[PDB]
View 1 (tube, rainbow, N blue to C red):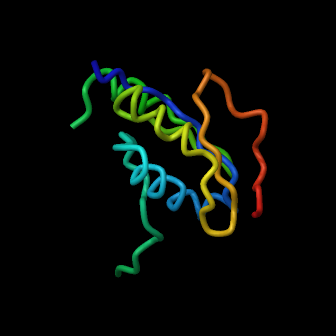
View 2 (spheres, rainbow, N blue to C red):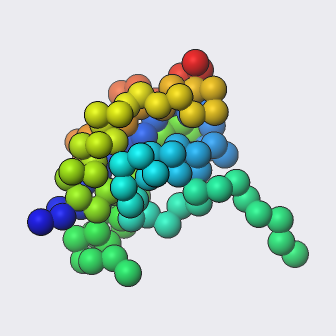
Length: 109
């Protein structure tokens, strides 16, 4: 009942644009348990054990990031609504299978 469920988000421009993929899919599909930024950097001078276990298996690359939705139904929403046009790129959501995606490039729209 609310099994945290891991999803790969992939296709955005570079690692400095990861935040938009996370924010956009979180707003569509539901809470993402990782604490990654949802906004660009700002200028300046609790998890269950199941959620925490999956959050701590962190993975990302230049154009993809693994996220943990708090339930399978939320993960399902993300995959169903994939792909999403985000900041000029097609960002896909796919269920995580314990490995990095075999498609790990930017996908410009």
